[PDB]
Image (cartoon, rainbow over all chains, first blue to last red):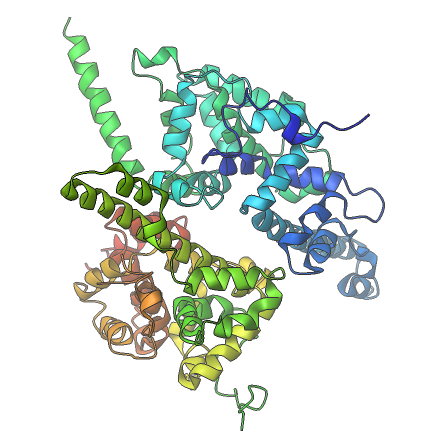
Length: 315
Length: 307
């Protein structure tokens, strides 16, 4: 079976091609799934797909980074403090407590290395045109549907949700100057804590249709799920993940807001997200990346809401 | 004969290279360090930039350095300009069109200079080897400035030093990778200096501290850029370098005697008051602390001591 080359494939159905200013940031909502695919591809003592990025680092630096990510941890039985505990002749109950604290510290120190060198790879390759080209083709060869989803394949022409997304999640000047550079989207999605946003949107009577799309694209879409244990536990603090948070912002494009323009409710999902992020200090901080004037715009919006409610009673 | 770094004393430094809190503190001079590398470009070559070759893929350093120092492509060869001259417009309409093309030609070049400058600084100043090369560049340029970045001849029991490292760094982030991004890098980068200076000058609690800040930003020659290329790159007159200099100058604050009356960290709370009254600076505060409005309320609402 001869592999279909990217340059051959249609690309007429994509509403967000590679060359779109708004593509690099949108694609980077799959950065953890992209890392997952590169890690999955390592078969036997090879660095797998990671090697396709060696041109983007100084000679030999790529190999170092890849290893630091996939290298098996040293056994916790060889830890100097572990060995000292097991030789100290402690009361059984105290020894076992100490041992668990050394085991947890050991895993945490491994997680810190894996995250550091993962972020060194991703921030080098996914913010460079040549590197995004390679990443685009890697995703295409992995799963055509996911490639499509990252490019808005078979999306309608007049999709009003797409316009709101482009308008509120990118700064016009920043995305025009360097599309491959850091965008508002990368800051908000990265700072946000998805679990608390999912809980508040589920309790919003306005955002019932939107929550249904979010629930499906986060939990039940098979190619929005990580294949490796390594990347899964790297992003997990029943349990939420950093990939689940990004997959929520990814899924936003599916929201239907064409019919709600007549009643001026077409941005209800966006203001619903703001009301789902204003509650806790982490997401509240994430909102100040999205819009520096969000608390003043929130009070305006609630003044006019109260102004309309008053005129409606007099009937 | 060459005065090697290995030979130098370094015993008076309270913030040596090996200190967890050094990398972030050094990167407050990141705009001055760019200025130094651009000063060194002499006979149509990249000067000090070449010392960082190993930290990029082969050739990459050459491209980046160029994109920063090179002369722009002549605007007489912009494709839109060529079409204006061929369209045969009225002289007055032609010249007005030509100015719209000229203005975006300059702006595009300011954006390319800034982009590739940021690409250099971000690669070399957040890596240990990169920081070694950078340390020696400043040492060979100015011994005093080298010392200032390391707290040369600073008191042992200095309290503003202990407050600074407690409020501008996260314990876990700074212990894991000192060379990586810290709260300080985020806060100083997002801050709008000109406004913070204005509020502290109106703040009666902070009067000694403002006099130090006004001197280290406007009077001190070592904290001033020598190149047009960098000072013009950081101009909105105020600059991004002047914002970073305000954070650098904090180590000079005399707060030890105010410990007894528990006002030894009044400079920090005064800074928070100075950058909470505009959208951009209060967004910068959320980097310094995620819980700052509740901490500011309980600290600035205890008027039971005023009774």
